[PDB]
Image (spheres, coloured by chain):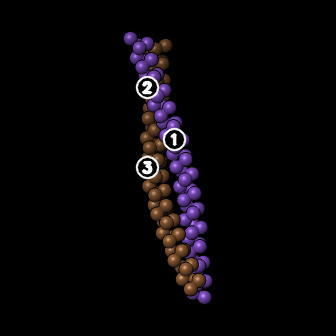
Chain colours: A purple, B brown
Amino acid sequence: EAEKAADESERGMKVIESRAQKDEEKMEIQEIQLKEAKHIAEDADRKYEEVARKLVI
Amino acid sequence: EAEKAADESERGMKVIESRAQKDEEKMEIQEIQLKEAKHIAEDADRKYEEVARKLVI
């Protein structure tokens, strides 16, 4: 009985760990995309303010 | 042997569940901030285009 319980717990542990690792990898990719979005936002903001100042002059 | 295996399996399942929930939260917040940043980027690009045209005029 104990052997059966241990094997079932082992299988559940392995599958849940695999799914967690894959979702963690995708989360890392999402963070990379967020960083790129941050950079794009900052660059565009600088563009806009510079152009507005030049237009005023 | 079975007792020790069961204890280790329980601890591993606990830690994997905690890490999985952490990953889900990180994925959610990453997606939210990503969408907000993309919308801000769209707004900035539109403003840049409009002010550039006015500047040429």
Label 2, label 3: how far apart the Cα atoms are: 25 Å
Label 1, label 3: how far apart the Cα atoms are: 12 Å
Query: Which amino acid type is shown beneath numbered disc 2?
Result: Gly
Query: Which amino acid type is shown beneath numbered disc 1?
Result: Glu
Query: Circle 2 is placed at which residue position?
Result: A12
In the shown orientation, is residue B18 left or right of residue A43? Answer: left
Query: Which amino acid type is shown beneath numbered disc 3?
Result: Glu
**Is residue A45 placed above or below B26 in the rendered structure?**
below
Q: Which mark is residue B28?
A: 3
Q: Which mark is residue A36?
A: none
**Is residue A42 placed above or below B32 in the rendered structure?**
below
First along the sequence among labels 1 and 2:
2
Q: Secondary structure at mark 3?
A: helix
> Mark 1 touching mark 3, by CB under 8 A?
no
> Mark 2 touching mark 3, by CB under 8 A?
no
Nearer to me, B18 or A36? A36
Marks 1/3 same chain? no
Q: Position of residue A43 (x, y in %)?
A: 59, 67
**In the displayed image of the protein, which residue is found farthest to the top?**
A1
Query: Which residue is located at x 46 percent, y 38 percent?
Result: B20
Label 1, label 2: how far apart the Cα atoms are: 18 Å
Query: Circle 1 is placed at which residue position?
Result: A24
Q: Chain of mark 3?
A: B
Q: Position of residue B27 (x, y in %)?
A: 46, 47
Query: Which residue is located at x 55 percent, y 46 percent?
Result: A28
Q: Position of residue A29 (x, y in %)?
A: 55, 47
Query: Which residue is located at x 38 percent, y 11 percent?
Result: A1
**The C terminus of chain A, quarter of image:** bottom right
Marks 1/2 same chain? yes
Q: Secondary structure at mark 1?
A: helix
Q: Position of residue A9 (x, y in %)?
A: 43, 22
**Is residue B10 placed above or below B29 in the rendered structure?**
above
